[PDB]
Length: 33
Image (tube, rainbow, N blue to C red):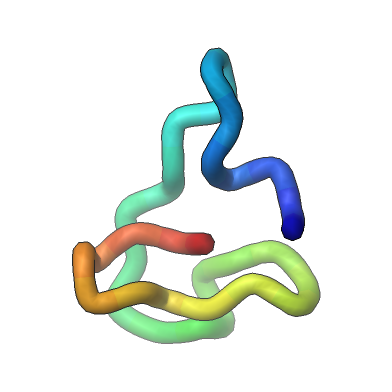
């Protein structure tokens, strides 16, 4: 998947999928992934 969940790639806080990279969604954790 996209680099929003790797060791040194902590996720991005989001409220919608548009806050995230392409193909990534805003998860229930409130973070991109």
